[PDB]
Image (cartoon, coloured by chain):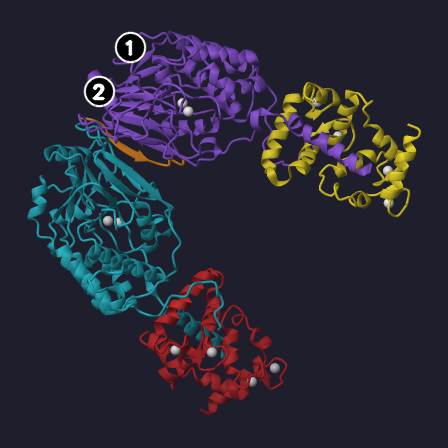
Chain colours: A orange, B purple, C cyan, D yellow, E red
Amino acid sequence: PHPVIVITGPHEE
Amino acid sequence: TDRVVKAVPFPPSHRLTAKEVFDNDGKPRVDILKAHLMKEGRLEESVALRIITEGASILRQEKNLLDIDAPVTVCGDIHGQFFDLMKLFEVGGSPANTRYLFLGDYVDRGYFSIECVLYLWALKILYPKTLFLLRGNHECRHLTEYFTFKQECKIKYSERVYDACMDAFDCLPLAALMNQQFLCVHGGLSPEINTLDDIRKLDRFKEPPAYGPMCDILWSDPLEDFGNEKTQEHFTHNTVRGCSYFYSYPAVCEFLQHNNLLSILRAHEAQDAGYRMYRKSQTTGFPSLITIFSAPNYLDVYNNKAAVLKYENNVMNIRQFNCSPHPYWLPNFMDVFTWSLPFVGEKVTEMLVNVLN
Amino acid sequence: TDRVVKAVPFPPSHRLTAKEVFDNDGKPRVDILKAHLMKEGRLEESVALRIITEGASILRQEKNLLDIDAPVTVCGDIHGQFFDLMKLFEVGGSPANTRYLFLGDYVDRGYFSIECVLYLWALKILYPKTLFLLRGNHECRHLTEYFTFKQECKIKYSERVYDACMDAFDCLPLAALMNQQFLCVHGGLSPEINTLDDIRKLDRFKEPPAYGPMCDILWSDPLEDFGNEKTQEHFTHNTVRGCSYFYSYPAVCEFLQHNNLLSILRAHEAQDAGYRMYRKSQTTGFPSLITIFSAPNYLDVYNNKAAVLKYENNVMNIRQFNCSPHPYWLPNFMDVFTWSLPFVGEKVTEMLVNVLN
Amino acid sequence: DADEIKRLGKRFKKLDLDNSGSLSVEEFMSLPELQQNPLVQRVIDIFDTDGNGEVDFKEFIEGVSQFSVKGDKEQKLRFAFRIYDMDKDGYISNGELFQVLKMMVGNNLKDTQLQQIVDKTIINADKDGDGRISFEEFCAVVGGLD
Amino acid sequence: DADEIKRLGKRFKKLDLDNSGSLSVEEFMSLPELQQNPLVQRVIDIFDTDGNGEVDFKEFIEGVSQFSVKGDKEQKLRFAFRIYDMDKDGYISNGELFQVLKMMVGNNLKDTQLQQIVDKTIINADKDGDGRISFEEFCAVVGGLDIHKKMVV
Ligand SMILES: [Ca+2]
Ligand SMILES: [Ca+2]
Ligand SMILES: [Ca+2]
Ligand SMILES: [Ca+2]
Ligand SMILES: [Ca+2]
Ligand SMILES: [Ca+2]
Ligand SMILES: [Ca+2]
Ligand SMILES: [Ca+2]
Ligand SMILES: [Fe+3]
Ligand SMILES: [Fe+3]
Ligand SMILES: [Zn+2]
Ligand SMILES: [Zn+2]
């Protein structure tokens, strides 16, 4: 029911 | 000319007029503004003044507690790091089609605080209903005087601009309820804030008090051992800040459950990864507290990454990014004459003294 | 000596012995193995066979559908890029205290496939319950014969080593149920697989068929226009692969909801960013499909980043990385004599013909 | 100055090793304290009124003259200006300010960093737009300091 | 066979521009083809049995004879081996293989790239571990190719 956490990066652009 | 380092870009000396910044519809040309500010250019004092006052006018009409719908990009501290702010927008999405929520601390420490303020205010004027700005503890007189913002204004513009900014900061909303599930603030909670309504009851149009509700929203921090506490004290005095409190995991959970909230999103503390997720609530299994920090390589020394939180339906995307290059400045925005003159004087005096022996 | 480019490292000629690779307790010395393979050194044929056969014994005991709990680092294609694999473990964490799940395609195209296999199998022997390996479509006889693995085994070792690998590949599990939320496979879905139990009924110990559930698991791809399809067919034949299918966004969504799953994690298709997240399911608001690709600068030409998916309950961290340096190899693993002799015999004969005419 | 000229003449004859009647750069670098002073070259060049490279007695006298408890602020500010005004045309240019600061900063600043702050100092004190600093503009900047 | 020497003799005379009795490198490079061939010098060197820098008639005859329908795989390969074996000591050293390969490959491969494949080539064929290549080991690597069949004139 609650949001999932997605960690991405370091987004160079 | 005899300019030595040709390779280095020379800042424009031309100051943008009202005509060039504002189109005849009253909307600011943010893209022109960006390109100019990025070259370390200045706007005519009166134009910066207009940007600041019109931005204040809009902020002044908003509520203490903003109602923000998802999707939205949540950002932490900026601290005058204008060049990292430009990249922050690449990473988080253009404000032209992206809703934004800033948690404060736009000024001080960084040497481009006025540009950050002018660009964000210009953006606020252009996107009144989709870009939001909250008050951080640095958005006040007491701190901008001790740190660098007051001095930055005096050297780049005038104290008149500083005063206008101080009035604008007084209008900054104190918090935001996002997607009806998240309480967003710069610092944190207060033992005097049990419901969202306690926030609405506050008088935010003023310099932050040294204690009380407003102060706590801007200055509190989670305990160092948040989530692994050995002291059932919900709120203990913050000796690190010199004011406000340290709030514990139980204190947050209580406020979350009582208010039917999922989590508290805040900034205020630097994070090597640009963010930090704390102990999950027992009731929802979702992080009870999340710290978001958007100043990459803070103070040019920490080499930390910055991050912003893109929230979509049931998906929280934390996006990290690194620092960008920025122009150099001497401490306190000092010019090379003031900086080197004392040394020149004593060195010429010294030379003549030794020779006359 | 005559050696011209003296700064270039020379591969050792000594072949690691059984007592050097395995100790008293029957555990592989992965650190000695790593260091030796990085210098392009070999193991004694028998030692290679032992690693391959022992790993196979372990794999043979596992189920078609593995049950992998969080936390875990999910990795995509490697394709014999051993030196990038070394980087992979550095970014994803030591196998000594990190659970891993590779989605297949360990061999072909890259020139260090056998090294990748020996290292992963040794790791499988050392960490039987924390390091998981799935079968990719390249882990079979048909493809390794056509591409490069077979020839690699023959030149560096022997066909016996090849056959042993083929036997071991037949033991490789086909899928994994990760944290009871994600279905993990190399390729994707099958019109013949409506539930997770269908995967359990399959007999995986054999060369993959040209059609059927096992083939689809290893070979399927999402539609090119996945998520934005005007194509009503859930499964359409894959003309790109020459077998299996193209599955649509609806097919995936129908399969996810029916099995109470959150998302499908797969590899099989190279990504410039090292990964890809497809359209969010309308039932969970979470990406319905995720492709993970772990071979950076694939084929030495793509200049793509590689990535691994580190996961823990509700927290997915996508870690990227760039390629690393690797030794040079002529096509088909040719030696310089076999490569030039045809040219030499031709040029000399060409000279004499003109000399005598 | 009348009897003082005699006092200085004494120090001039000792400093002037070869007794050639003028002071060279080498003869100034003979003193232990001036060998570590980054402004030695600037002061000599300034004293060197006819730009022949050496400092004769006349220039020595007039040079030391600039400094006197009697000298007013304007005299000290003017001398300070000469320190930066390398080619002596009366205007501190971008390149000169850079080179004079470079002698004082050494390697503590990167060329790119020094160039940026030099450009920023000028733009803010360049009230007439020629990209150079006149004496008037100079005084305006270093006005209330001391 | 008596006719062969007469033909080879007339041919030798033609190539012998200045008519001194021997053939210099300068004269071989007079031909339009024998100047685009990166292995011409290597062939001249091998034909040049006494090492005087030139090729006399007898050497010309012995050289050409290696490439005959009368010869077998043995001598054909020995001639092949001699191309790589520059100092003629009966072994192919690491440097010699690199240099000869550099001649044919030119700049299409970087030094580090060519060196690495030279090392792996030697490691693979060097059965006694002396770091070099003997004729026997050479025959072991290049024998099933049957290159000798195309080495006939
Ligand atoms: Ca002199
Ligand atoms: Ca002079
Ligand atoms: Ca000048
Ligand atoms: Ca000027
Ligand atoms: Ca001749
Ligand atoms: Ca000879
Ligand atoms: Ca030799
Ligand atoms: Ca040998
Ligand atoms: Fe802050
Ligand atoms: Fe693949
Ligand atoms: Zn703060
Ligand atoms: Zn594949």
Residue C6, image x and y in percent?
48, 66
* Residue C233 appears anywhere in the view: no
Label located before the other in sequence (1 or 2): 1
Residue type for callout 1: Asp
**Left or right: residue C344 compared with residue C142:** right
Tell me the residue that label 2 is attached to: B254
Q: Secondary structure beneath disc 2? A: helix
Badge 1: residue crowd in 10 Å (few <14, some 14–19, many ≥20):
few
Q: Is residue D115 above or below residue B186?
A: below
* Residue name at image x 90 percent, y 31 percent: D4
Instruction: Residue E138: name its quadrant.
Output: bottom left
Residue C5, image x and y in percent?
48, 65
Q: Is residue C171 above or below residue C271?
A: below
Tag on residue C112? none
Instruction: Residue D11: name its quadrant.
Output: top right
Residue type for callout 2: Glu
* Residue C168 appears anywhere in the view: yes
Q: Quadrant of the N terminus of chain E?
A: bottom left
Label 1 in the same subunit as label 2:
yes
Tell me the residue that label 1 is attached to: B198
Quarter, ligand 3:
top right
* Residue name at image x 52 percent, y 78 percent: E44
